[PDB]
Amino acid sequence: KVFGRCELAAAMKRHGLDNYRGYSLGNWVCAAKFESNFNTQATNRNTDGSTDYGILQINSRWWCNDGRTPGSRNLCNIPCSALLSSDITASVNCAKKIVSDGNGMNAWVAWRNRCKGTDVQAWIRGCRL
Image (cartoon, rainbow, N blue to C red; front, side):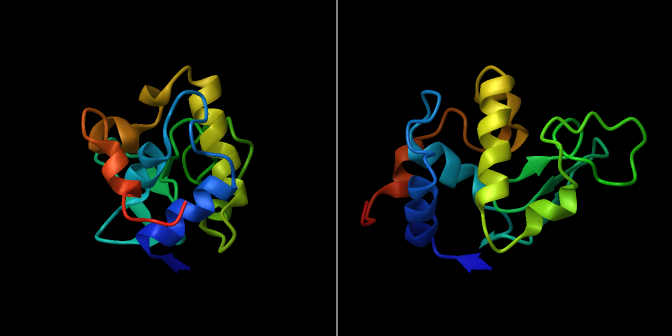
């Protein structure tokens, strides 16, 4: 499923991400944007050998089991491919765990590299929420 920006912000807010663990909604929307799109089925391969899966760009090193890398810690207890669902609930739940268990959003590679330091609230401006 593809979302538009405000559509996705509204869905993430409905799922409790606004201000979760201290992070305003735009942080989460920011880290979802990949290859010019918001797509539940997207994957981003990284040069460190890991891959970011799905709408919330969850990284396979620690958080999900990609089925290929031996010794995967799989902290969200989910196959990575299962984060490519049309319903965002599993991805939300895993992202909440990243930030909570990982002690802040520096634990989320996509956000750390692509969103940290920017005016993240721009991602939710102009939307019904």
